[PDB]
Each structure stands twice: as structure tokens, then as C-alpha cells.
Image: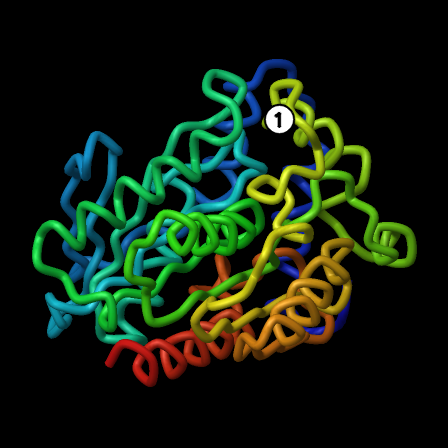
Amino acid sequence: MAKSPELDRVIGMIRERAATPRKTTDDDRRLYETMLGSMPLDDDIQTERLGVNGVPAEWIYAPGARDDQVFLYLHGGGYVIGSMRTHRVMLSHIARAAGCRVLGLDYRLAPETPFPAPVEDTVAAYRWLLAHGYDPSRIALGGDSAGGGLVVAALVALRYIGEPLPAAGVCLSPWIDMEATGESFTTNATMDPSVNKERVMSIAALYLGGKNPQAPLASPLYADLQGLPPLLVQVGGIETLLDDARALTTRAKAAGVDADLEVWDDMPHVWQHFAPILPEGKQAIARIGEFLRKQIG
């Protein structure tokens, strides 16, 4: 929607998906995979499927990776869609930029398994890393949209159950409010080509399975954020989720957490997916990589 042939092309891919007629949950899952499926994994990327405390997962790393540094990654999709199939290319770029390993979780999705399953899964996976000799100071959690919010909820959960906390969290267009009350849901409604308030609320109802929409672990907008490690938050200027990112950063700082927010003008929801064809994607990922090298490197 802004000018730049590369951005034009990305917006086109996003608008095509948003306008493609769908019926079933699995249709929605496949359509997300389709949008992101024209951008292949680099030949030199290593991947490995494995279970981590029962959670299906995937190591993703580039040559020269530090096998003792781990970015534990939680994909977006409203807790209903998404997988390593949609996210592995982006994670491979992050891995190469940070020089670390990415552990991506194919965590449990709704409606099959509702809230708080993904929080449980993140905890199990983190516990798996600790049990396998990985150092808390060399682990960071990352996620986008639902995953961004999950990063926060999981960090809170870990503190609440006394686990030694990771070095850092990365939140890409985090969704932290099940009720979509942020003002940007109104102001950015015609600007955002992929996320809207009606979509978010319907998905929230699927995830919640009848549980309280303001539960702190589903909506960390309401969670106790004391004690969390440094956060990097990125979000696009045209996003309806813009005020979620701002609220998170404000609530974090108020709780004493070192949080830094970057608002990237003209960027759509999780534009980092399109790094292979989008300069701003590469730049934002380079910035994630710097932050990770600082915190776990």
C-alpha cells in the first residue's frame, strides 16, 4: 500500500490471501502455508524434526551456528493456524543473522486443544532445554503475533513456577489482548491489509474455549510483568495490532523491564516473513540478530 515495488509485491501476496474464499479450519491453515510457500529454504540451512518433552519441534540453523545458543521460537497464527511450514524460512534468516540455533515449536493449536495448551508447551520445551544442558543465559524466546504474546505469557509462567529465566524475549507484532481493545483496531482498520478486529475476536473465541478473555496468560495485557528479562518489540506502523505492541512496551517498562519498541513505518503484520523479497524484512531481521547477539551471544 506504500510505494516501493518490493513492498507493493508483499502487500499483493497478503491481499490475495485475505481475499481467497475459505471454509474449514484446515483450509485456513493451508492458505497460510500457500501464501508463504513460494519462498524456499536456502540450500545450506540444516533442519531436524524432534520432540522436546513431548512437543513437536524443529532445529533450524545456518552454517557456523553456535550450538549452545538457542532462540526458542513461537509462531503466530492466532493460536489456530501456522507451523514450521509457514515460519521456517523466516526463522532460518534470524538464525543466520544471530549466528545461533533456532528451536521452533509446532505447539498445540486450537480449536483441537485450547488455551492454555501453548503456554504449557512452551514451558515443557524450555524445561527440555535446561534438562539438556543449555544455559538460561544463552536462551532467548521469540514469537510473532499470537507467538509474541505467548513469549510474554510464557516468561511470566516460568517466573511463577520458579524456573531460571531466559536472557531475553523478542516480540514481533505481539497479540496481548484477546478482546482487541487497542485504538489502532479502529484507527488502522483501513490501513492493515491482513488483520482486523472481527478476525481477531473470532479467533480469540476459538482459542479461549470459553475461558475468561482477560486471563493474564491469554491476555498478558493483564499479567504481572515483574522480573522479565530484556524485550525487543517490533511492529508495523499500519497495523491494527500497533497499540498491543505499545501497551506491552509501556506495561513492561512500568514493571521495571528493559523493553525497546521499534515501530516500522508502512510495514504490514509480521513483514519479516518476506525478508527474502523485502529490504525492510532483511533490515528488521538484522536488528533482531544484533539484539540476540548482545543478549545470548
Q: Residue 167 appears at what percent x and percent y? A: 33, 71
The quarter holding residue 240 reads bottom right
The quarter holding residue 192 reads bottom right
Q: Residue furthest right?
A: 187
Q: Residue at x 19, y 35 (%)?
A: 53
Q: How is the image coloured?
A: rainbow
The residue that mark 1 highlights is 208
In the rendered image, the vertical position of residue 92 relative to residue 86, given as above or below: below
Q: Residue 281 appears at what percent x and percent y? A: 51, 69
Q: Residue at x 72, y 64 (%)?
A: 247
Q: Residue 209 appears at what percent x and percent y? A: 61, 19
Side (left or right) of 215 relative to 149? right
Q: Nearer the viewer, residue 121 or 10?
A: 121
Side (left or right) of 123 relative to 216? left
Side (left or right) of 114 relative to 55? right
Q: Nearer the viewer, residue 126 or 170?
A: 126
In the rendered image, the vertical position of residue 272 relative to residue 47, given as above or below: below
Q: Residue at x 21, y 30 (%)?
A: 54
Quarter occupied by the N terminus: bottom right
The quarter holding residue 251 reads bottom right
Label 1: few (<14), some or many (≥20) within 10 Å?
Answer: many
Q: Residue at x 27, y 40 (%)?
A: 124
Name which residue type carries label 1: Leu
In the rendered image, the vertical position of residue 119 relative to residue 1, given as above or below: above
Q: Residue 38 appears at what percent x and percent y? A: 43, 46
Quarter occupied by the C terminus: bottom left
Q: Quick one: SS at disc 1?
A: helix
The total of numbered circles placed on residues is 1
